Image (cartoon, rainbow, N blue to C red; front, top):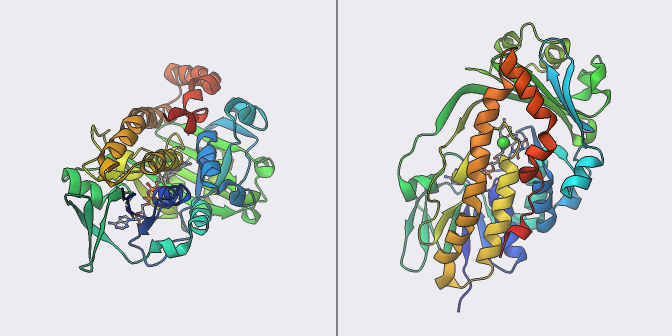
Length: 381
Ligand SMILES: Cc1cc2nc3c(=O)[nH]c(=O)nc-3n(C[C@H](O)[C@H](O)[C@H](O)COP(=O)(O)OP(=O)(O)OC[C@H]3O[C@@H](n4cnc5c(N)ncnc54)[C@H](O)[C@@H]3O)c2cc1C
Ligand SMILES: [Cl-]
């Protein structure tokens, strides 16, 4: 009984993590990534306890300790007055409650740590997938350059515009939010004038029509920011935050060339898997960035999918892909819905609804425990 050889399309967090996770449990997995080399851009992400646990399982948490940063609190700030509307301490309480720390870190750092632990030799650069056809015993991936690679299982981790998803279920439009995210890492030495940044904090500035998130990365030496605005040029971004507190305007004014990303997600899908092909990460369940969980969820996907594929033979692959999907879909669906809800919530004008939002924010540790406190390993059979 042959154990499956596994081809993974995409070398982002999701693809690296699942390849790394498969190999750690004795399955041969190989990544096909379209880019000629992996980027060192892409700014900051937040790793919750739930994702931290996935990184421990995959053996990469120890390598990320240095470049991680440990926000002491989540501080929800009024757009105009700069007052702390709601605050929750993370130092100690977060780890005690949910079983692991809250980290903020560069995307690229997480990507690099995964790449190293997996081994770069397991990643084919320059391989752009254009398609996947199911065979009788497995599947074969088509590349742009005419190539092919057959396998006992194929995992589509090729992002929100997944070639693998298109092949399996046909054309499907990504859903535009009507907002853009501007993202940047600002060196802290360009922000000496901003005294709030003396403490490491997860900042969430909430206001009318738009919002602004900031946090430290690289052990406190740079500050990530994400500015979500109705929909790139720095002048138009600075203007969209006219009237806001100096903290926001000063941080925006310290980056000449921020990155702009139209923010899309997709409707939840009833089906991810077809014979020996399945999806993972943004390809399976793309969400807006408003829970800070997309990477976290790709990591959960990776752990769970590696578990099922490490325990089967070639003939058990379809069943294993369906078991992964059946466990992962409901959770990701709720996060998708939640991330949409939060886009609205973060952008209310001043008024009763915003005051009611603020009230429900007081009970946030209970209300999001299902996310941060989730034990991925304990969810398995
Ligand atoms: C502004 C913003 C802020 C965010 N903040 C957070 C946060 O705080 N916390 C969090 O957990 N998540 C966050 N996310 C979400 C997170 O970045 C993603 O969910 C996560 O990186 C998705 O990883 P992935 O591997 O599924 O996909 P991607 O990172 O999209 O990787 C896909 C890979 O596949 C490759 N590829 C694509 N098509 C092909 C092809 N046809 N053939 C071969 N290779 C291909 C790409 O080159 C890429 O390397 C944020 C997202 C945004 C937009
Ligand atoms: Cl996200």
